[PDB]
Length: 185
Ligand SMILES: Cc1nccn1Cc1cccc(C#N)c1
Image (cartoon, rainbow, N blue to C red; front, side):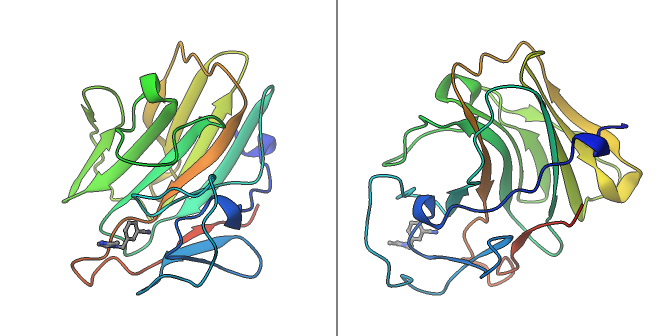
């Protein structure tokens, strides 16, 4: 891919974060805390999962960013509609306004309904996310493996402004404490 030149500076929106997340001062890193982080509740916060949105809203153009997933056992990444449900249980699917991939129990899957098996030979330490709003495309790249394609959602029906989407995952195992980090351009 030659998508690097649509690079955008993404920062995390504290106000959308699950109340257990800790976002760094620079708003470029997020990790799961071992307790409630002493913030008030609001209608923006993801209640059931360790999720947070980027501050940026996209309704046009081409956008690229990279996320560091080093030493994590579980995570979700991609984009979602600004109007996605925040409270209660839900599945990550394009019908619900999400265009995502994830790692769970040693397998990588795309958030289709039902989910799609991914074929990755080189476990990624960094993921590139490309969005072409007009084309209706969301693509994922393996930065660790020379930028190799992981998955392309095509014919996407965004149906509104898009926000960068992150899930740091639970840490029941004690092996998933590491942060998601937005990588420098
Ligand atoms: C109340 C509770 N029972 C089990 C675990 N937790 C903490 C929790 C719940 C939902 C999302 C997050 C995050 N992020 C943390």
